[PDB]
Amino acid sequence: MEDFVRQCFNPMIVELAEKAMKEYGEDPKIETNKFAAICTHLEVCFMYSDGGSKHRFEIIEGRDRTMAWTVVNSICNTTGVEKPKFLPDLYDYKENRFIEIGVTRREVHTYYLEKANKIKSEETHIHIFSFTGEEMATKADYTLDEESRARIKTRLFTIRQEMASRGLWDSFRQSERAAA
Ligand SMILES: [Mn+2]
Ligand SMILES: [Mn+2]
């Protein structure tokens, strides 16, 4: 799975995923399913931010934690928006809300509810994607146009297929279940 990951995702994403795992004492060489999952989440977040007009989104995911919180603080102080209890992934300047992006090998609603109960926010928008083409978002407000979401859905299905091709999909799907 480690070698698959390193040829599936761009080096910039792979590098960000390794840094994030080390900060949590996780070895990318051993917890390779987590490694794939983290890269996938990064790629989706970056694809999503590209789906809007040029200036639309502040990107929080992929930043160093301290600077991430600094940018979050800048947004909150300048917009009035409630400060999230956990680091969100993007801030949407058009809709004026933080966005938590999820990617799940489980059902979208199960994951959605876990995320909603965790963050405890009446403001932060939640948008969940699956490896089956399903999506679920706060109030059925999907933020992006259909085209931008579809591209993301397509990419996730390709990753799933590329994994299944190598006999890695079953283990990858099961890993999230065991973790939860
Ligand atoms: Mn996140
Ligand atoms: Mn996320």
Image (cartoon, rainbow, N blue to C red):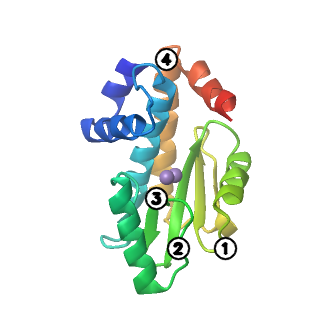
Q: Mark 3, residues whose alpha carbon is within 10 Å: few (<14), some, or many (≥20)?
A: many
State the residue in front, 140 or 10.
Answer: 10
Q: Quadrant of residue 3?
A: top left
Residue occupying the point 50% across, 55% down: 149
Quote the CA–CA distance across marks 1 and 3: 16 Å
Q: Quadrant of residue 176?
A: top right
Callout 4–callout 3 Cβ contact below 8 Å: no
Quote the CA–CA distance across marks 2 and 1: 11 Å
Q: Which residue is mark 2?
A: 83
Q: Earlier in the sequence, mark 2 or mark 3?
A: 2
Q: Earlier in the sequence, mark 2 or mark 4?
A: 2
Name the spot of residue 25 as percent of width and height, x first: 44, 32
Question: Which disc number belongs to residue 122?
Answer: 1
**What amino acid does circle 3 point to?**
Asp
Quote the CA–CA distance across marks 4 and 1: 41 Å
Up/down of 37 relative to 58, above or below: above
Residue occupying the point 40% across, 55% down: 61
Secondary structure under tag 3 reads loop
Q: Which residue is mark 3?
A: 89
Callout 4–callout 1 Cβ contact below 8 Å: no
Q: Earlier in the sequence, mark 1 or mark 3?
A: 3
Callout 2–callout 4 Cβ contact below 8 Å: no
**What amino acid does circle 1 point to?**
Glu
Q: Mark 1, residues whose alpha carbon is within 10 Å: few (<14), some, or many (≥20)?
A: few
Residue occupying the point 25% across, 35% down: 11
**Would residue 7 be found to the left or right of residue 48 on screen?**
left
Label 2 vs label 4, nearer the camera: 2
